[PDB]
Amino acid sequence: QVQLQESGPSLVKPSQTLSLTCTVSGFSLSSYSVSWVRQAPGKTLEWLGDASNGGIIYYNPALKSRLGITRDNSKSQVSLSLNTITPEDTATYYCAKCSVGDSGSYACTGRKGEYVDAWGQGLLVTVSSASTTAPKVYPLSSCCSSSTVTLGCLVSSYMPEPVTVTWNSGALKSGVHTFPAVLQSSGLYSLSSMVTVPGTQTFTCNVAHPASSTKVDKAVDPR
Amino acid sequence: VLTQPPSVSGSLGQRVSITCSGSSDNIGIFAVGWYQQVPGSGLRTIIYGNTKRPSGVPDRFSGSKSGNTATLTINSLQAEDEADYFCVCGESKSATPVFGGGTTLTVLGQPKSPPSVTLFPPSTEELNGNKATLVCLISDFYPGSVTVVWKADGSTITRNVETTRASKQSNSKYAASSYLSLTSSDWKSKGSYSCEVTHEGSTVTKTVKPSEC
C-alpha cells in the first residue's frame, strides 16, 4: 500500500526554521521522485520543490533562497526545511510521490516528465509569534429589531486551540450555536458562540481553555 | 495562475464540467492535470497529460483541452464526488507548475437554504481596551459557499477582515463567520457598518450604527 506521511512541528514562530520529514512506505523511495507542495488556509496550491530520483533537487525559484530539500534513501525519508518564515507560511504541507515514466506532465518537477501519483496526508503548520495565551471573553448583544434577542460571547485572542463553550453551565442547550475559530493577524485565535432565545432569565457563557488551565464565565445582559 | 470558477453544483447521476482557463504559455502548450481534494481529506490525482486517468480512477472522470482551456468532466455524479477540484499545468516562462484556484463541487442532497446573518457590534468592555471587533455570524446556508463584503458608510472594507471557510453544521447545512478588527476610534469614526453575505446571487445584509450602540 503506497503511503507518505509528513511529520514535524505544527506550530512555529516567525524567523525560525520550519523542518519537516516525509516517511514513505509501500514503494522503494530510491526509485521515485518526491515533491513538496503546500496549500494556504484558503488559497490554492503552491509547488515547493522536488527531490528527483536522479539526485537533482528542483526548487520553486520564488522560495529557493529559503528552501532546502534533502533525500535519505536508507531511511525512506525526504526532508524539507524553510527558513525566515512569516505568518504567510501557514499552510498544510504535503509530500507527494511521482510516477516513473515520460508522460507530458509538469506536475512532479518543474519540467516535462512525470506526474504526481500519490499524495501524503498533509501536515498543517501554523506560523505565529504567540505562546500559550488564555482568552479574553467579551459579551455580545444586538442592542442597536425583532422580539427574540440574540446574545453571545466573543472568545478573543487565545492560543492554542481548542476552547469549549457552554451556557448556564450546560443547562441552556437549544438555540446555542458555537462557531469554528478564526486565526487573526495578531497570531491568535478567536471564536464566538451565539444563543437566540424568545423575564428574569440570565445567560452566562462558560469558556474553558485547557492549555492555559483557564475557565471563564461571562454574564451577558439581554437588554 | 489559471482560473476556474469558485464553485459548481450538480445532480446525482448526471454530468457536470469544470473548466480551467489560462494562456498559450501554459494550457495551450503544456499538459494539464486534475486533483480531487475531498472535504477534510487529502489530494487525489484524477487526470494527467490532459486526458489520462491513473489506475483506479473510474472512467466517469474525463479530461479535455481546447485552445487555452482545459476541462474536467464528471458523468453519473455520485455523492462521493463532492470535492474541491484543482487543475495543474506547466509554465513556459517559470520553472514551477501553476495551479488553478479550485472549484468546489456540490452534489445537491438537500433543499437550498439562504444564510442567516447576525452582526454584533463591539462590547463596551472591549472598547474600554481601545479595541473594537465586529462579529458577523452566518449559519444555515446550503450549498456551503458564501462571499462576505464589509462596508462602512457605503465604502467596501478589506483590511482587518478575517473570514473563516464554511464548515458543516450538525444539521448538514453550513456555517461561517467573519471578523472586522478595529480600534475604538475607527469604530466611532463611521456612521454605519454592514456585513453583506451573498449566496447564489442573493445578498443578506445586517447593519450596526455606532451612534445607536
Image (spheres, helix red, strand yellow):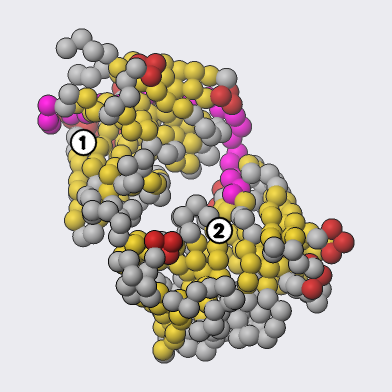
Along the viewing direction, whichever of A89 and B11 lies nearer the viewer: B11
Q: Which residue is mark 1?
A: B208
Kindly identify which chain the residue marked by label 2 belongs to.
B
As drawn, the residue found furthest toward the left would be A146
Q: Is residue B172 magenta?
A: no
- Tag 2 near tag 1, CB within 8 Å: no
Position of the C terminus of chain B, as image quadrant, is: top left
Question: Does residue A146 appear to the left or right of B59 in the view shown?
Answer: left
At a point 36% along the width and 40% down the height, the residue shown is B170
Q: Which residue is mark 2?
A: B42
At a point 49% along the width and 18% down the height, the residue shown is A215
Secondary structure at badge 2 equals: loop
Give how far across and how far down residue A170 sits, in percent.
38, 19
Give how far across and how far down residue A77 sits, in percent.
78, 59
Q: Which of marks 1 and 2 precedes in the sequence?
A: 2
Along the viewing direction, whichever of B182 and A177 lies nearer the viewer: A177
Give how far across and how far down residue B45 sits, in percent.
56, 70
Region rendered in magenta:
A124-147
Q: Is A116 located above or below residue B173 in the figure?
A: below
Along the viewing direction, whichever of B64 and A88 lies nearer the viewer: B64
Are the residues under badges 2 and 1 in a single subunit?
yes
Question: Does residue A69 appear to the left or right of A134 in the view shown?
Answer: right
Residue A32 visible in this rendered orientation of the protein: yes
